[PDB]
Length: 175
Image 1 (cartoon, rainbow, N blue to C red):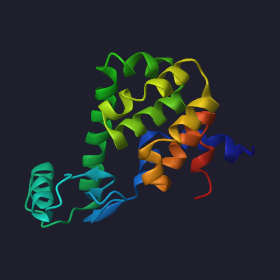
Image 2: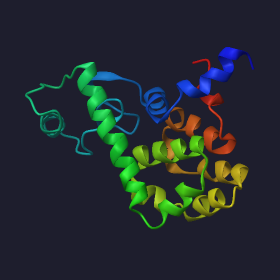
Image 3: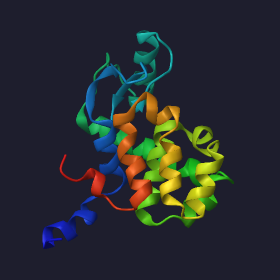
């Protein structure tokens, strides 16, 4: 690793990680599962109704957006959504002990997983949670790769799975 390479971990954090996995879009679009999304992975609604998505958007931002937001608004919403995922882990009796056992990089992977799937989805993966607590990284990554979350939308999840396997930021290098 060069001096620059050793600096790369200091540039990565949960925000930059999710920003790479989710992208940044200023107009409502459908994600890989067909759900209306905006910003940095902000899922607006699971309803097939674009009007519902627009109503949820206006509520989230606090103005009449007509389906479009600014980069600053996307960043603000993203920070709220990341804070929500962390809070959701820490108040959950199943997820908190696993999260606490993880190193800093895998804790980002955990927050990312919860941001993408929600708390009950993540807390339902009984075997993966035990594998992570037991530091069985290869087994945890193989089992994550069986999930519908990964298999239905591999490009958004693959980086996170690698990060659970290695505890490094290597999957986020050289985009």
